[PDB]
Amino acid sequence: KKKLHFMYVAAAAFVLLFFVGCGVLLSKKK
Image 1 (cartoon, one colour):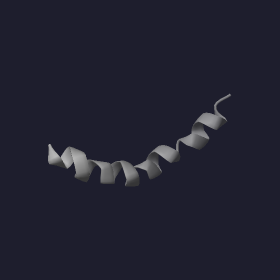
Image 2 (cartoon, rainbow, N blue to C red):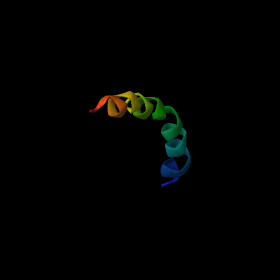
Image 3 (cartoon, rainbow, N blue to C red):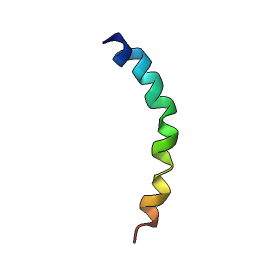
Image 4 (tube, rainbow, N blue to C red):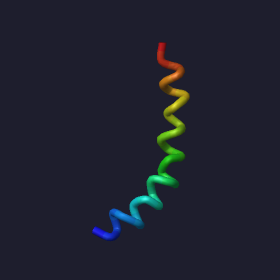
């Protein structure tokens, strides 16, 4: 469970780079 608290939050910070790359995809949808 502790892994979901710290080891996880640390992920949401890095993995964010993959979620931000989709931003352009949405703005492209027309």
